[PDB]
Amino acid sequence: TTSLDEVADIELEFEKADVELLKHQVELFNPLYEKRANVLRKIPKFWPIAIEAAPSDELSVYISPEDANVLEHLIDLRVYRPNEDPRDIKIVFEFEANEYLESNSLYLEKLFRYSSQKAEANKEPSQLISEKVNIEWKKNKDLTRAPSFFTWFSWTGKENDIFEDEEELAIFIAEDLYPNAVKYFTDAL
Amino acid sequence: TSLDEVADIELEFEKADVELLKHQVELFNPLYEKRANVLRKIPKFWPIAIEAAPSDELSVYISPEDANVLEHLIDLRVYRPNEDPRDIKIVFEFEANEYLESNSLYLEKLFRYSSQKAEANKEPSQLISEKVNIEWKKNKDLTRQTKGTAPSFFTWFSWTGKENDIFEDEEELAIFIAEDLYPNAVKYFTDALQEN
Image 1 (cartoon, rainbow over the protein chains, first blue to last red):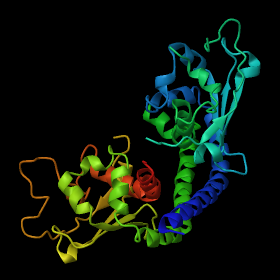
Image 2 (image 1 turned 90 degrees about the vertical axis):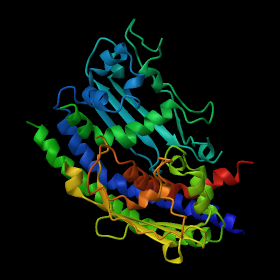
Image 3 (image 1 turned 45 degrees about the horizontal axis):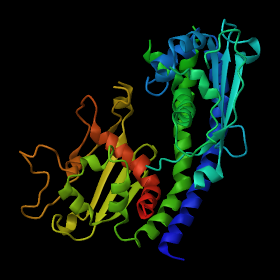
Image 4 (image 1 turned 90 degrees about the horizontal axis):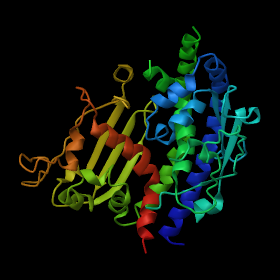
């Protein structure tokens, strides 16, 4: 067992501490977020304003002028880490009634699961996989057919192992947009 | 208003970030010490990891001559030794070389989180620091450059943040060392080791 072997093993210990730390983060921030979320819902167009105020190259860049008409009715956004593996992120979008989305799809939920295999096998690592989230577009308002922001909901990451815009966006929502929504909104004044 | 309620809540988030960082420190302190003991057995680990780290955050500030000094960097440590876990101490240790006198082989730079500075242009300046004295051997002082306007990496040690600028690249570098290079060092090293 070389020093090179020791280092790789110790790195596995760091991964476990990372998971322990996220567990603690989950306990800490869940009540704060729930409490924040029910105040934010009373602030008209809080989320499209915060998204617009967020760095455009992180999100705004992917949003059509038409995508923006849908997102104008985004009334709620939430991020969860609901699984025993705290690295899985669940992102929720809720829209008020509008001209584009059938009312079944006014609530859209997407789950990104940490993958052992994908993480194990540039090399800026891709770690996340997801299931296609179905959207019922109103006839005939389907922006999924430049590309629409809403195509992000079909991404799976199971086709290759490149770290793509969709996965990076998922992390931005979870680790930046969501914690900082209030700062971004206030920046907008 | 319901926007002044958001305010009160936002202060709770701020208390929680700090609580969370405090837990992080107790959690990782011994892991870093264990890791550091093994890394010291691995020659050139730090210059190899510095080199493999993203160039746009680090090696861009490193002239070839700087790099030559860094070939002799035998240890790098980051501490959060104070009450406020946002205070960072960054420690460089060098083996003997042509550039540093023996009492500058150990270089220590502390950054304090200043809430007054942080209260006052998107990732605004939050840290303050003291100049770290470096004793250079005769005619080896890399910070002494008039022409050749690009500052040696080593001018970073004199940054204080006590008088403010628009951006503070130096602070950005400090955070990168603390929050990216040091935690991801083994990952970076491994990328190089396995660029086969």
